[PDB]
Image (cartoon, rainbow, N blue to C red; front, side):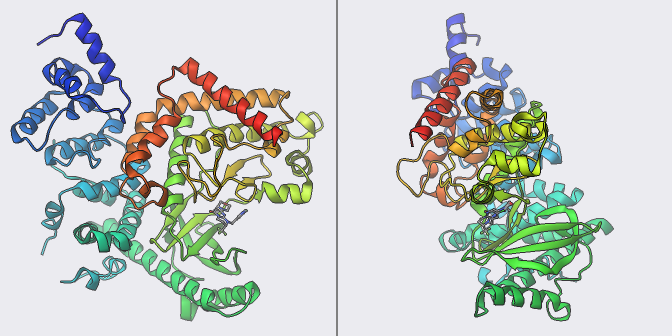
Length: 553
Ligand SMILES: C[C@@H]1COCCN1C1=N[C@H]2N(CC[C@@H](C(F)(F)F)N2Cc2cncc(Cl)c2)C(=O)C1
C-alpha cells in the first residue's frame, strides 16, 4: 500500500518527467504497484494513464475505478486525455468533465485543438445524436443556410452545449468545423472522419433551431456570415480572372463591390465579422478596397463597423491560412500567459481566420516593414525620431516608444525561437509608430527554413541598432526581458505542448512532415533539462552567440 522513503523519492522523479519522455516497462510496473498512494498527486495521473494497456479490458476497467478515486486533474492536464493517445470513452468523458469547470475565455484559448480532438471521438455516438446518401451530395457551406421546417457528455455534445449559451464561441466552433468539412485530404484519405464533421455541423445546426429566440437568431447570423463569405469568394475569383494589371484589377474589385444589387457586399444588416465576432459589420467600403503587390492577389478590405469604425482586413483567396492561424493562436495564448504573470510585452497577436482550406481573413495592423523603414528613413532610430520625437527621451526618441520597442523585440525573440520560425527577413518584420515590433508570414515554422543552416535565434543588426547598440541601458533591459519571458513561458510548457500534441493530424504543412517529432521540437526549445537559473544563462548565451555572429556577417 504505502511505499518506503527511497521509493517515494523514485516515484517523485517519474511523476515530474517531461510529456515526450516515455516510461520504461519496469518504470511503469512501479507506478502501477503504488497507484493507490499516487492518488493524492494530481500530476501523477498523467504518468499513471501512460501505464495502462486499453486493449486489456480488465486493466482498462481497473484504471477507470482509480480515475474516479484520483485527485481531480487540471484543465491544462485534461487536454492530454483528449489527444490521439487516449480513445477509451470513459477517459475522454473525464477530460470533458474537467473542461466543464473552465470559463469560456479559457475554452476559447483551446477551441482550435478541441475541434481537432473530435477526430479521436466516437463517430457513431455523434451520428446517433441526429434527431429525425453520398457525403459529396451534402455541401457543408449549406447546412446552416438550409434550415428544415458528472461524466454524461462527450466532446461533441459539450462544445455545442456551450456554443448555444455563448455567441463568440459558436462563431469559432462553426468556422473551425466548416474548414474541417472543407478539408479535401480528410475527405479523400478518411471519408468516415469527413462524415463525422458534417454530423457535428448538422448537430450544431439542429441544436440552434431547437433553442430560444436568441439561439435561433445565432443560426440566422451564422448563415448570413456563410453567405457573405460565399459572395466575397465569388468577387475574388472574378478579380483574379480579370485580365490586366493591378490597376485594372482594383477597378473591377471596387466596381463589383460598388454593385450592391448584384453583389450585396457594400450594404448589409449588422453581422458578426467571422475574424472577430465581437465586431459587427455594415459591409465593405468599395472605394478603399485594393489588391496587394503579391502574385496570389490578396485584397485589403475596409469593413464599416457598428459604431462608424473601419476594420481593415487581408482577404486571401487561393491559399491555406491554417498554419498562420495556428501560429497566431499560439502567439495570442503566449501573450495572455505572459500578461497573467503581469508581463505585458507589447505583442501584436493579430487575428487570422481561415474560412476554408482555400480562403481566409487576416486582421490588418497598420505598420511599415523594417525593410522600407531603412529604404526611406535609413534606420529604426531615424524612423522613431521622425514620428516619435522627445528631447529628454533616449536617443532623441520618446520613452514609451523606446520601451514598447525593447519589450516587443524581447517578446518576439523568445516566441520566434520557441516556435522555431524560419524564413526571417526585413519584408516580414514590421514596425509601428508606437514602437511595436512584430513578425508576420508563418510559412516556415518548427525549424523549417528555405535556406540551409538557419540560426536558432532570429536577430539582426537593424534591431540592435534601434536599441542604441549593445552598451545601451535599453540593450540591458532587452536581455532582462528575454530571459524573464523565457522563464514565464517554460512555466506553461505542459499547456503549449498538450495543445501542439492536439495538432498532429491537423494537416498543417510543417507539422505533417514529422507529426511524431513535432512536440519534442517545441519541448526542446524550453530546455526543461535546465533549472531556471541555468535557463537564464542558456538564454544569455543564445543572445551573445547570435549578436557576435551577426556583426561578424
Ligand atoms: C494581417 C497582417 C498584420 O498586419 C500587417 C499585414 N499582415 C500581413 N501582411 C502580409 N502577409 C503575407 C504577405 C503579404 C500578403 F498578405 F499580401 F500576401 N502581406 C502584406 C504586407 C507585407 N509587408 C508589410 C505590410 Cl504592412 C503588409 C501576412 O501573412 C500578414
